[PDB]
Amino acid sequence: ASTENILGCALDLFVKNGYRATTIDMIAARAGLGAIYFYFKTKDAIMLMLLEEAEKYIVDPIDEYMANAGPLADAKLVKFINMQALLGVTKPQHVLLLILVSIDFSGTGDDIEKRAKAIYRRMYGHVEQLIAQGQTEGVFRSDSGSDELASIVMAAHDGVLIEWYRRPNELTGKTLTKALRSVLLNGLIV
Amino acid sequence: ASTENILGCALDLFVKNGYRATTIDMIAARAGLGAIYFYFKTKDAIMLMLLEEAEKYIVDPIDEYMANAGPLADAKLVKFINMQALLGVTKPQHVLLLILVSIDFSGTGDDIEKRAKAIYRRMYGHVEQLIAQGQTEGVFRSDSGSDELASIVMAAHDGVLIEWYRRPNELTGKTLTKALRSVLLNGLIV
Image (cartoon, rainbow over all chains, first blue to last red; front, side, top):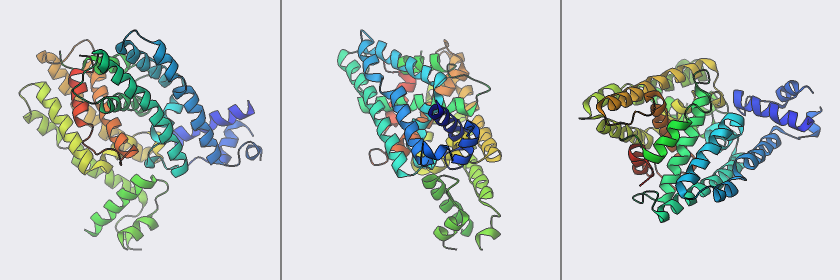
C-alpha cells in the first residue's frame, strides 16, 4: 500500500506535469514520505513499473474477453470498444502512458519508450486479428488490409482518450463512445 | 533564413527529445550558431512561434479549401482528409505540436498549452460545421451529434499521425490514408 501509494501519486504527477518535470522529491511529498529510494532506486524504475501495471490492466485481459465475445466479429469489436471506454473512465492515466510513452515526444528515453512500444504492439495485434476474422466471416470489408484497418481502430481510440485530456470540463471518458462505435462500424454516410 | 534555420532545428529537436529536454544550447549548436538570444529571448518564445507557424500551415487554410470542395459534404470531408494526410507527410512536426502541446503530458506549461488548445478548437470547429452541413443535406447520419462525430474524425486523424511517430520504419504518412477515409465514410461492416 505504501507501494501503491507511491505508484499512484507518481502516475498522477507524470500525467499532469510530464515525465521530465516530475521528480522523486515531488512524488515523495505527494505520497506523504529517503523512504522512496528504498522502494524504487529511481524515477525510471517507477515508470517501468507503471508500464507493467498498464500492460496488466489493459492488455493482459484482451485475449480472453475477445475469445468469449461473439458470436461474430462485430460483437467482438463492440466488446473491445466498450472495454477501452471503460479503461478510459477508470484507468485513463495508464492508457495515456501506453499511447504516448511509446513515442519520442514524451521525453522518457529509449529504454522506457521501447517497453511501451512493445506493449502497444501486443494490443494492436489482437485488433488486427479480430479484423482479419471478421473479413473471413464476411462481416467486415475486405477492400483494405486488416493491418491498416486495425490501425484506424487503434488511432480513433487513442485520439478519443487524448481528447478527454484536452477538454475535461466539456466531456467525460464516455461521452464519445457511442459515436466512436457508430463510426467504426458503419461510418458517417447514410 | 537564420530565423527559419533556428525554428526548424528547434522543431526537430522538440519532436525527437520533447520540450523539456531541449535547450537553446542544443538548438544553437544544431543550427550552427549568443546569437540565438538576439532572435528569441527564450525557448518559450521559440515554441510559441512554432505554434503560430502551425496555425498558419494547418488551420488558416481550412475555411477556403472546404468552401471550395464539393458539391456535397462527402467531397468536402474527403478534401479535409486528403489535406491532413498531406500535412502529415510534409509538416508532421507541426501537426504533432497541435495534437500534443494541447495536453498536460507534453510538459510545456499553461501559457503554451492554452495557445495550442485554442488553435485545436479552431480546427475542430470547421470539422463540426462540415458534419452539420452533411447532416442537413442528408449525406451524413443524424443519430449522433455533429460535435461528437467531429471529435471522432479529429481523433482518428490525431492517432494516425501519432502512429507514424510510433513506427516510422513500417509506415509512411500516407500508408493509412485510404483506410482512414474508408472507415470514416463507410465503416468496417460490409
